[PDB]
Image (cartoon, rainbow, N blue to C red):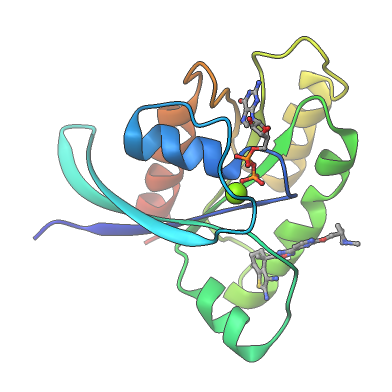
Length: 168
Ligand SMILES: CN1CCC[C@H]1COc1nccc(-c2noc([C@@]3(C)CCCc4sc(N)c(C#N)c43)n2)n1
Ligand SMILES: Nc1nc2c(ncn2[C@@H]2O[C@H](COP(=O)(O)OP(=O)(O)O)[C@@H](O)[C@H]2O)c(=O)[nH]1
Ligand SMILES: [Mg+2]
């Protein structure tokens, strides 16, 4: 049977979670997508010759630490922690998202990838070295992406699938 992978995209508002997810689903750059819409989207993909079913949850809205929201996030098997390379605050928030994932999954080894988005822009404020060194502190991969140009989009999602496969 075809394996389904439940992936969750997290990070500050405005980093490009929706743009990244829609590039994967539609193969098109969407510069405008209602910042309040949180929803899930499926796509069949060939990753290393195997057709698998991705189920991507694109998160949005206010932080809520209810038993219901924890249960909803606990459905994720792997997480993309996204920041924007021209927004220092989004990068400085990443540790919070990682700590919340570790708590809900009750595990120090949850499949995760650090994503530096907006790599097409010239306004960089977060050095690639600092981002690579944060992923090294966590023991996870780092991928540079652009939802505008498609840079790194399959690398981010497919690497997360490969981290889930090794975790099982
Ligand atoms: C002063 N703040 C703290 C630093 C940044 C600043 C603002 O932080 C901020 N803003 C919005 C959302 C979040 C946020 N953190 O984790 C989560 C998720 C979705 C991640 C996945 C695992 C869980 S489990 C659960 N219940 C969640 C929820 N709501 C989550 N989202 N953080
Ligand atoms: N140049 C550029 N802008 C992007 C990129 N990804 C998203 N954006 C823009 O960043 C803003 C926020 O994007 P959105 O996908 O709504 O972020 P979300 O709140 O994390 O879902 C919008 O103005 C998008 O056009 C990218 O890689 N490059
Ligand atoms: Mg969004």
